[PDB]
Amino acid sequence: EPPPMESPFQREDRNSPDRFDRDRLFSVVSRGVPEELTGLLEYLRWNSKYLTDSAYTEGSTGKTCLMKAVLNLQDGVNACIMPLLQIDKDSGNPKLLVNAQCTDEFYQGHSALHIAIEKRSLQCVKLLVENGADVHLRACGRFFQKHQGTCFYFGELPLSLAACTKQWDVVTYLLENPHQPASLEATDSLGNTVLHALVMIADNSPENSALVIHMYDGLLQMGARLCPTVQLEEISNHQGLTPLKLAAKEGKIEIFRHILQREFSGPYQPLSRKFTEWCYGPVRVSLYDLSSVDSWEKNSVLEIIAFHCKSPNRHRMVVLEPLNKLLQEKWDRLVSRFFFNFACYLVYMFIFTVVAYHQPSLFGESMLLLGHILILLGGIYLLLGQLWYFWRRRFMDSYFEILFLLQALLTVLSQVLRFMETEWYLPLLVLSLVLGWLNLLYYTRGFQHTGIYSVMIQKVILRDLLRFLLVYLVFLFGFAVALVSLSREARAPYRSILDASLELFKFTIGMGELAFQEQLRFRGVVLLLLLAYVLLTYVLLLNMLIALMSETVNHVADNSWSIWKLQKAISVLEMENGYWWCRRKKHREGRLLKVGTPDERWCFRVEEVNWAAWEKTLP
Amino acid sequence: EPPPMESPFQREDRNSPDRFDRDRLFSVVSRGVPEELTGLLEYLRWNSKYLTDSAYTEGSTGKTCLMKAVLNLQDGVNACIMPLLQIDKDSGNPKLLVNAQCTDEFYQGHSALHIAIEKRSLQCVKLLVENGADVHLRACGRFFQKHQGTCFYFGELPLSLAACTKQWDVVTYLLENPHQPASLEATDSLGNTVLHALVMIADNSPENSALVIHMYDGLLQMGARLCPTVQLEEISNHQGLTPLKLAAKEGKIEIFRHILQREFSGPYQPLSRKFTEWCYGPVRVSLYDLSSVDSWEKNSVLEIIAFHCKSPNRHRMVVLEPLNKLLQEKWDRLVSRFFFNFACYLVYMFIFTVVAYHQPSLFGESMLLLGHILILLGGIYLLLGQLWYFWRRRFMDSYFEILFLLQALLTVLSQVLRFMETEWYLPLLVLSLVLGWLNLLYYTRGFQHTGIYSVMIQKVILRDLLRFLLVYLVFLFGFAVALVSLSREARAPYRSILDASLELFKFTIGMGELAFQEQLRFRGVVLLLLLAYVLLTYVLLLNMLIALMSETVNHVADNSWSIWKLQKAISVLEMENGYWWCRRKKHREGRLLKVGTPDERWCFRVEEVNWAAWEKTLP
Ligand SMILES: C=C(C)[C@@H]1CCC(C)=C[C@H]1c1c(O)cc(CCCCC)cc1O
Ligand SMILES: C=C(C)[C@@H]1CCC(C)=C[C@H]1c1c(O)cc(CCCCC)cc1O
Ligand SMILES: NCCOB(c1ccccc1)c1ccccc1
Ligand SMILES: NCCOB(c1ccccc1)c1ccccc1
């Protein structure tokens, strides 16, 4: 268990002229008086130690006397910090105590400047900075990393901590002091910068969103005038993302939306992304920026939303522009490939159904052999394509992206059984055929009127059905074992465990026997136990029905269009790569315009019409 | 792709003493200074060109320099417009540049006056009008026409555009200027007048409704004093409608309600429609106006609501008065025809059932032959009536209006089979019989206690059932093909595709086999595939049930009375024409009263009692 960093009740632990112990030092510093600090210098120069040694620190963490001074800050000002740092300078230690930090696993690197910044005191921050404290000390402990349980994640920097805490004066003093200037370009471990730490502390609540949007714009505006020669929104962390991509991956929708369509009028225009070129009543035409939003480059916002994301908000980022217009422009160009692919799959499935039906038992024979050869070639091509897709991609939207493989694999496996002349090529093949018709359902995603209907009608969750089936199946097996064990002595029904399981399952499709057998010694108890099974199956079925109804009473129904748009987006980004043998050359979208200053950016126009805002701007 | 009409970033395109190119002209006009316009006149008189030629315009659209001047309007005033028009006048061109307009397809006819009116600047409008610009220039491009996608529909006139934008000062200046007076009577393409364009931009939202009601009343009041000799609410567009009928057709309920019962006290009384004659406590008697609201004339509000309308708000216009009282007065007079028609149909159906039941296999014989003759005559009369109804009418309310035809057609077709002595007159006839009993259900619309019950009990949508049946039927056919293909090799059930389809459908009515067949080589896989079919049919049925319940949970239930009133209104307006052989003379309803001034109007009194408003007017 990690010790607390300061505690008024639990004392510190030493576990790793006059005598002046560390306990008296902590006692006089915690109260906060400088008169009783006399005699420290003479004692240190007699014992030939330094104030940052192992004697004067909590050995379990590494907390020095200065951090106890700052942690006992009363009314924002401590009168002991200045003489303590002065006598530390007079001691002549090589390692300065102002920038000392802990060495424990929990609070590694946690300096005094972080404590002074968190205590919302500009005076202690000024006293620490003016006495030679570096402003790039990283807090690398487990307590300052994003994980479940007890943690407070910030960007492991004094400036990041000042940014996450909404205090503006401390951010300004760190950014433009003469004694020790910080930098917005400085990075911690995991590669994050201060524009990343704001994104990773965002939330979908409106207050936290307003906080992080305001402070993100503020830091970007100060980065415009402090270090204009560097693009602050293009520095990459160790995963390879940028702040826009990191907003896309984590599921933070609000700061992602604000970053995607921010606009500042005036001198701060060159760092905008949404430029409006004309507007006529309700219609407004805006030139959005496709820098790392299109799929022509490497991992971008579209692919990160499509594949590398696990969040319930991955279906609402697609709807907001300029992702909606971009994916609509991609779909209106690549719908022909989808329809031709669907027609080829339908022709392959028709020839499969013909071969499976008109088949001899164990010109027409030559036609059927050509059909078998064509089925084998189609199955091996589909198998190669699906194995390519999995190997490149190294969850319900991927559901139909695995069954294809089964409809491939079984098929080719069935055909090698046909080449082995066994008596099992007929089940697996026709089993494949059943799966194949189910596998056609994915191709409803390409048409509007049936795609919206499919997304609207999928009103049950798969995990609920697969849990209920498992519970009912264990129930059936247990009662089947009991019924076989009960009916062994004659005065025959329920002879084996499988037959008794079938005759028990027959009560769910609606045809059960339920009578005196007149062949069993214990036929009354058999009837009683069957009555118990019926009365329990009805409770289980009613519970499942009630649970599904309670699930479907209270949810919003507007997500149908968003989910359909996401499914179409995944299919578009899949087809944009091309086939595994005819790799499609990626076509850059947008036009290279000149906005501001020679600032040449890729731009993409969208024409949005909205009568409500136009009615609002009217008198 | 159409080019933008102005764009600060994308430059214009030429695609269709000192030199003074069009690029320098656009550069100096866009900034907005007049000092650098010097030397233009000498250059134009040396090169013998004009300022509106092809050289000085964006050839892709036809945009002139003046429209670039107005589109770069800063703080409402440009100092360049006045010298530009002055030097255009000094150039001596035959075609004036002030009223020049585009010639592209997308922005056809879009003048500078439209831009100045949209920019909400009275000063630029005054400068354009005073320098000789006609006020009847029509914007005929696709961008200014009502269609899906990107469009801004107004009445293609400067006055209509000033009317749709809620600005009052520009409307007044266009209406009463001495330099170039506009007119409320002027019409664009599609025949619309200014009062029509207000209706076609209306909406059911309260803010837009309040805007359009206020501005409609305002323009009507100004039309009272500018051009009193013309009725502004009687001009017909090219479809033949008036503003009231256009409000009825499009589904705009709020402006339709306001137009139907507007009243102004004082000097503006003669243009009202609802006159109150007396009011005593709560009861109030009002003389509404039946000008184009009754069905005695040509296409009126009642017929346009009844037939020529496709909107979800066609069942709420009937409930609001004076349509409610009018249709109640029609129904209380024409209920006898409905009941006599129902009794005649019931007698015809009883004789049909008797003939279908007491029929010999392949005095009583003469009676049955007379019954057959009467069935043939009734069927041919009903067929002639229904063919008349379709040919004159050249959707669920029309559903029962087609099945009659089938109950006609099959019947007469069955009888000609009886005259052909074939072995198929017995199925079709009795099939007709079944349909006819279903065809009786439409006649529940005439009685209150069962009509409200029928409208209340119709709680399912037909398209959902017809989609679910299609999905389940494809499912059944696919599994039937698989089951026939699997069971071919003996060690018999499931022999043909139709029999296997029937034995698979038997799991839905609640009687399935589900056992080891002991006759098939692959009987275990047959059992497994039947289990798969059962487990999938239950998922599909549960999904359909959940979807219907979710559609049922969250909806308003007050629409039963409105839908029943609409159905009764459709039946009344159908019977008012009369039979196809005894065309009923149309009877004018209301009385010819004299209200205001000799203003003789058809009027219809309604007695409305409402305790709530009377409680509000009390202290
Ligand atoms: C309302 C339910 C869920 C069913 C509806 C069908 C009928 C006949 C019985 C009801 C029922 C009970 O009312 C109570 C139990 C629990 C007692 C089990 C004793 C072994 C089971 C049980 O199926
Ligand atoms: C709760 C439902 C919808 C039914 C209720 C009746 C019973 C016995 C089974 C349930 C059920 C599953 O719980 C899961 C599936 C999907 C797995 C199919 C495997 C081929 C189907 C499936 O009918
Ligand atoms: N009064 C004789 C039956 O009328 B029905 C009826 C009677 C009173 C109130 C409402 C309806 C009726 C019964 C079943 C279906 C439809 C109508
Ligand atoms: N148009 C032919 C059938 O299309 B379907 C359809 C038609 C119109 C609107 C919506 C869907 C369809 C029917 C059942 C299931 C899925 C789709």
Image (cartoon, coloured by chain):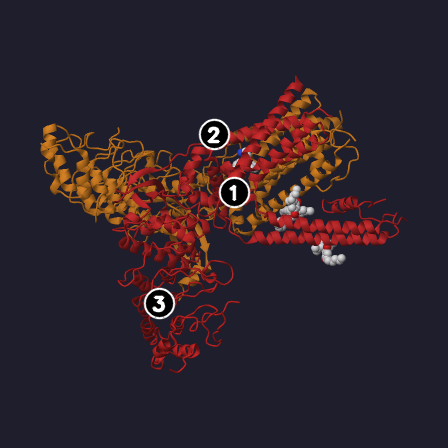
Chain colours: A red, B orange
The 10 Å Cα crowd at callout 2, few under 14, some 14 to 19, many 20 or more, is: few
Q: Position of residue B23 (x, y in %)?
A: 19, 35
* Quadrant assignment for ligand 1: bottom right
Q: Badge 3 is on which residue?
A: A96
Name the one closer to the observer, A510 or A45. A45
Query: What amino acid does circle 1 point to?
Result: Arg
Whether labels 3 and 1 share one chain: yes
Q: Which corner quadrant holds the N terminus of chain B?
A: top left
Ranked by sequence position, the earlier of labels 1 and 2 is: 1
Q: Earlier in the sequence, mark 2 or mark 3?
A: 3
Q: Residues within 10 Å of mark 3 (few under 14, many from 20)?
A: some
Question: Mark 2 and mark 3: span between their CA atoms?
Answer: 64 Å
Direction from residue A612 to residue A391 in the image, left or right? right
Q: Nearer the viewer, mark 3 or mark 1?
A: 3
The disc at residue B181 is none
Label 3–label 1 contact, CB within 8 A: no
* Distance from the alpha carbon under mark 3 to that under mark 1: 49 Å
Of tags 2 and 3, the one toward the viewer is 3
Q: Element at badge 2?
A: loop
Instruction: Give the residue drawn at x 72%, y 46%.
Output: A508
Label of residue A582 in the image: 2
